[PDB]
Amino acid sequence: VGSVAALLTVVFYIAAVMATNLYGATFPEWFGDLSKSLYTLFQVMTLESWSMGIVRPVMNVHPNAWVFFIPFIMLTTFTVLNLFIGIIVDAM
Amino acid sequence: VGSVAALLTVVFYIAAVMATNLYGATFPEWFGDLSKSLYTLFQVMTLESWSMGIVRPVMNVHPNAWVFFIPFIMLTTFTVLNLFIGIIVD
Amino acid sequence: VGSVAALLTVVFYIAAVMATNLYGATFPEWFGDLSKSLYTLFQVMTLESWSMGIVRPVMNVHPNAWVFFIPFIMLTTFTVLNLFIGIIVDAM
Amino acid sequence: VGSVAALLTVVFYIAAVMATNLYGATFPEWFGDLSKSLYTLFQVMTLESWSMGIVRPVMNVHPNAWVFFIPFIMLTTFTVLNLFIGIIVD
Ligand code: NA
Ligand code: NA
Ligand code: NA
Ligand code: NA
Image 1 (cartoon, rainbow over the protein chains, first blue to last red):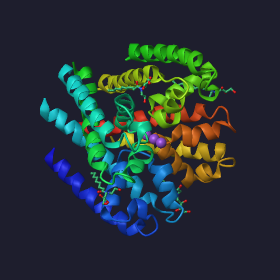
Image 2 (image 1 turned 30 degrees about the horizontal axis):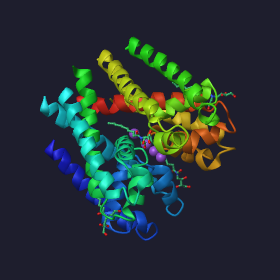
Image 3 (image 1 turned 90 degrees about the horizontal axis):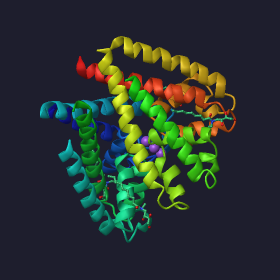
């Protein structure tokens, strides 16, 4: 439960560092600094406008942006699901 | 199960009171009164257009709005998940 | 499991009948006929653009539209969750 | 768990082949090639803008497009839920 939250924080920070470098110059409102990137990757994790709002516009400059975002989604969404179930199971 | 629904209603009302005060003047369509706020925070909880539709436009006036909305999402979505599982288990 | 799918079909049809009558005249693209309504209520159940795309525009003509849509969401989303878990539990 | 991931990959590929043929000519940005189709069907599976962004605009050319997309959603979202629970249980 604690290790799951620790793995998610580390992965979320590493990805936000990676995103700032990759799309920061071309998409500064979404990835211009670490803070902007952490906020965008939280939104992407909630699946809110991830494709129409973020990744499709990013792919028009970086055609392989999906190699970062789709595995990011698949990982964080599974980890969050594993985390929330983990708290509920430990409570019972 | 009942206490979970009670905790969620209290938290949802407190947050709706907080939102009306914070962004009611600058965003009156989404937070102009308690009723408008309760409706918006229900939408934010369902994750529908929370960032592109609500929080990014709010952050252009209030840059720290994320300190209210991200913890609100993390709390209510976990509580709802705990509530729905609670009914199914019982 | 079967009764859950039966309850969901009945509720989904009743709601689609209710919506066609309520918002069909003022929002004919989303609720103009039973077929259009069933499609919109399926979208509303998946939570896709339910508020920005459907219910906020509907509330500008019908201010109490939320009395129909919010309880519809709370019911169908809980029933679907109960249905999907029901199949998985019965399979094991 | 492995067979669930195998069933999902096969179904996802078959559907992406089907979509390219069906709406590739009329919607080339979303279904112009197998790669574009696989990306769109992943988005549709996450429920992101599936109706307002994809299926409503597709239905204005192909009125029965819902016969492909609604069953696609019902299948893949159930399979993914079955997959994620499968890993956690194991
Ligand atoms: Na959305
Ligand atoms: Na969504
Ligand atoms: Na969702
Ligand atoms: Na959206």
